[PDB]
Amino acid sequence: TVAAYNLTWKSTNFKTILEWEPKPVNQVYTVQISTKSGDWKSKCFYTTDTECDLTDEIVKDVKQTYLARVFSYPEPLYENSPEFTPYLETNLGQPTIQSFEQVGTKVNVTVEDERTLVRRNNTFLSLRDVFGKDLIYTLYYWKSGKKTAKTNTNEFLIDVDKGENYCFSVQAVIPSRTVNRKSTDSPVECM
Amino acid sequence: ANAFLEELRPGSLERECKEEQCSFEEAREIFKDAERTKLFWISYSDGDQCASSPCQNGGSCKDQLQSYICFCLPAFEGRNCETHKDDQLICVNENGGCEQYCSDHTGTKRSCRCHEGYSLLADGVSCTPTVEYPCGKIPILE
Amino acid sequence: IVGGKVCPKGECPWQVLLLVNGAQLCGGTLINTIWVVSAAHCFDKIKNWRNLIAVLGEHDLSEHDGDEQSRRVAQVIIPSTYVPGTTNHDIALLRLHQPVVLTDHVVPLCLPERTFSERTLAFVRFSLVSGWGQLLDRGATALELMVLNVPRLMTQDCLQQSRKVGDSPNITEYMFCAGYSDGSKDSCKGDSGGPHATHYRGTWYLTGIVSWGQGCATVGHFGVYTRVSQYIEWLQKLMRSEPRPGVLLRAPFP
Ligand SMILES: CC[C@@H](C)[C@@H](NS(=O)(=O)Cc1cccc(C(=O)O)c1)C(=O)N[C@@H](CCC(=N)N)C(=O)NCc1ccc(C(=N)N)cc1
Ligand SMILES: *[C@@H]1O[C@H](CO)[C@@H](O)[C@H](O)[C@H]1O
Ligand SMILES: *[C@@H]1O[C@@H](C)[C@@H](O)[C@@H](O)[C@@H]1O
Ligand SMILES: [Ca+2]
Ligand SMILES: [Ca+2]
Ligand SMILES: [Ca+2]
Ligand SMILES: [Ca+2]
Ligand SMILES: [Ca+2]
Ligand SMILES: [Ca+2]
Ligand SMILES: [Ca+2]
Ligand SMILES: [Ca+2]
Ligand SMILES: [Ca+2]
């Protein structure tokens, strides 16, 4: 048997999967996850895949810091994963402009409040429900010259030249963050 | 798409990329600017990865750039919701819900047992003392 | 115990005090009314094998009360593989000459089945270690039973996180580390043979025995305990056996 290596965390909107190497040959795996003071919980028992979905475990408290490890079977050989703090590290999904209503010389751009894997009361909490004030959306627009706007909510109220057409693109941002501070630009929409 | 002579007509995002599939060039003819065209083309041409309907057991697929995300039903988990949370009644999984001892069994379900001085209750998972002072219990707290 | 707290009287009912010639010697754990699990090195320099006393229901070494029960140690069984002055197989099974009375202050700790202990308890993060050992490295011993909660570590992590020492003992499959490497909390010399009890769903189990370590609560070092799960069978076969002539007995292992 050979100890797993290159343990990586793939997380977007809290959907968190742990991946690793190599392609098991005559060996299966079992994962364990935990917070620094909690007990170790096993997952993906004797799997032959080189991945393990840990979403349901980390969403129990996205502000905790988890450590995961992969056992190897033909104490057993294992490899610890990097520490993971969902709230501080989960990638922000690609936003989606929900719509834009013009009213005179201004335009209201609305950003769809996408849902995350965080469950609560039999429902999926939005990115806003989770991050609250830590989340902002920046707008990148041009007269169909670069322009930008920022909002602490899910909407932008901007000015526009009557008659001319505009195109918009948005990004989710968590200013306080250091890594994975911004999401990828949303699809382009033109009024 | 390009039909005979339509190109004489100015560029139109609607008529060209919405009501039809437009090439990068047609797109570049509407936006003109390079970056603006690229910012548009990344998503427009990315293709919906939710088309395979990868999310199983009644899950919901959410499209992303060159990837997707599955939202599963309570009883499910896994990248594509392929894991049944009700098919993990094995001992190494939280002691198989057993209060004390757990014993695996191929095919059938695991069974629970107890330490001397205790007996298995009817739930088939709990143990209860059968003496006045069972091991591991603290009298002045019980 | 370094960096711990007093175990409220009655909350460590399986703790045993081992005395030789009436002098404090080591700790222990009651697993039934007649047997006590302790450490083997605790008997490295014993000479008066008829002077070994085990006390249960103890708490304050300076005040006698009716919860205290004394019993002569009728037999000390050590693995034939254990070597005096060394660390491997640091375990001992003591047969009390007469059964102790179970009370609110004297109760045994459960000896778990091997697999339950390896597959479940071994992953319960925290467990309690206790005894009347030193309150500081090279310091004096405690008058009141002290208790401490320590986190368990798999050996790979213990070695990786420990500082190498001049030909220090290897951590075998018969051992396991627990504690902290920041020099704040750990068990100590006089706590030897004491229990490393794990709480799991309403019941406490014996998972370890205070055995050895680089000094007491030394920066970059963890406490080392005997992995009791490796001796379940050994203990069970012995407890169903007939007492031998002399006090000391070396039983084969496996
Ligand atoms: C040589 C390495 C090692 C074998 C030795 N280390 S030590 O000397 O640093 C232990 C120690 C610590 C503090 C004071 C003293 C002392 O002798 O005064 C001794 C050591 O540990 N020796 C053994 C006995 C060896 C025998 N005679 N069979 C020992 O002292 N064990 C008791 C003990 C229990 C818990 C802890 C703890 N959780 N940390 C530390 C010690
Ligand atoms: C649907 O398409 C995605 C694209 O990445 C693929 O990963 C799935 O396996 C397929 O079912
Ligand atoms: C998408 O989300 C999943 C969890 C289910 O509720 C589906 O019915 C829904 O479409
Ligand atoms: Ca065209
Ligand atoms: Ca056309
Ligand atoms: Ca055109
Ligand atoms: Ca057309
Ligand atoms: Ca149209
Ligand atoms: Ca052209
Ligand atoms: Ca053209
Ligand atoms: Ca896509
Ligand atoms: Ca006393």
Image: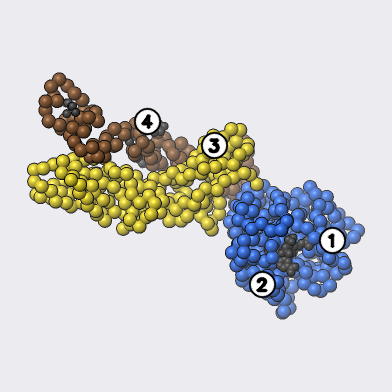
Chain colours: A yellow, B brown, C blue
Residue B113 x %, y %: 65, 48
Label 2 near ligand 1 (CB < 8 Å): no
Q: Amino acid at mark 4?
A: Ser
Tell me the tag on residue B52: 4
Q: Residue at x 46, y 43 (%)?
A: A17
B82 in relation to C23, above or below = above
Residue beneath the point at 62% across and 61% down: C220
- Tell me the CA gap for discs 4 and 3: 27 Å
**Foreground of the two, A33 or C62:** A33
| Viewer-proximal residue among C28 and B121 | C28
Q: CA distance from mark 2 to mark 3?
A: 48 Å
Q: Residues within 10 Å of mark 2 (few under 14, many from 20)?
A: many
> Which disc is residue C75 wearing?
1
Pointer 3 indicates a residue of which chain? A
Q: Which mark is residue C135?
A: 2
Residue projecting furthest to the right: C245
Q: Name the residue that disc number 3 marks.
A: A22
Q: Indicate the secondary structure of the residue bearing disc 1.
A: strand
Whole-number angstrom distance, CA of label 3 to CA of label 1: 53 Å
Q: Is residue A75 left or right of residue C74?
A: left
The quarter of the displayed image where residue C15 is located:
bottom right
Q: Position of residue A96 (x, y in %)?
A: 27, 43
Q: Residue at x 52, y 36 (%)?
A: A49
Q: Quadrant of the C terminus of chain A?
A: top left
Look at discs 4 and 3 and give the one toward the viewer.
Answer: 3
Same subunit: marks 4 and 1: no
Q: Quadrant of residue A3?
A: top right
